[PDB]
Image 1: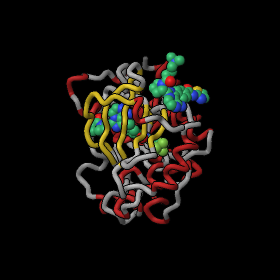
Image 2: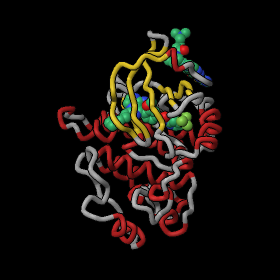
Image 3: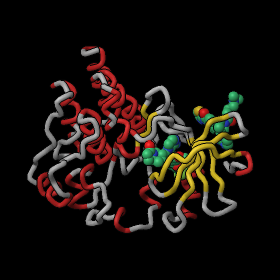
Length: 265
Ligand SMILES: COc1cc(C(=O)Nc2cc(C(F)(F)F)ccn2)ccc1-c1nc([C@@H]2CC[C@H]3CCC(=O)N3C2)n2ccnc(N)c12
Ligand SMILES: CN(C)CCCC(=O)N1CCC[C@H]1c1nc(-c2ccc(C(=O)Nc3nccs3)cc2)c2c(N)nccn12
């Protein structure tokens, strides 16, 4: 799955993403691609390169497509599908889009289809959130960075007490016992639906991570975003059951989202 770095033409700087600078470019001059230059010393390179090869086999219309890697040089390059509208979090925050609620539900649906596919391959995302989803030129949302938190060397991102750990997207059993499962991705998906319907607000926006972890242990939850109907709110709320085995699967969530789309749309 090695891409010859000479087949790449760099056209525009997209900014600093998670763990490296990204550029827009062409592969063989004709095909649009995004090129991420992995920050040196930020990943467990041998483990990361071993997993990157297995992930080229994961393919779904709602997963950002991995095209190949350039590892015969440093920094390492990762070549993927170009997502012209950038990260979902910044896309939600641009008030000029004047999103209809049908568009917000379609974004949830896109992510849910990607997660149902990863769940079918017994593959955990481990850091699902709007900052990790990307948006293409047609407004289609796709999931990225699935499983990458495992190769991050900086301890501030890795452990529950860390300053960069996704406390606001974590269920009680993750915060208390480091119990990761498909049900911790389900909880994070409910939080992501909340981010979409809140147009990119920070979950628990008036709390610190420490206060959020206490609110959750007491059984308290995020409350209904103004743009979410009662039926949409029931779906995101079902992801936050205190008991992990009572939370739905991504297949069940997909069926519920499609039912609401047919009813409302
Ligand atoms: C090449 O570009 C990317 C690659 C990956 C990536 O490598 N993902 C990945 C890789 C693997 C593995 F194979 F390496 F293991 C497994 C799973 N996922 C993830 C995201 C991008 C990526 N990052 C950005 C922007 C960076 C600046 C910020 C700031 C503002 C904005 O919109 N941003 C988004 N993009 C923009 C457009 N297209 C992209 N594909 C992309
Ligand atoms: C027009 N056409 C002929 C040219 C096609 C355009 C083309 O070749 N492109 C577009 C830009 C980068 C470059 C590129 N694409 C890929 C790729 C694409 C799709 C699938 C897939 O869909 N896999 C699936 N597996 C299972 C189900 S679907 C698997 C691999 C790869 C690759 N593996 N290494 C190197 C370069 N690569």
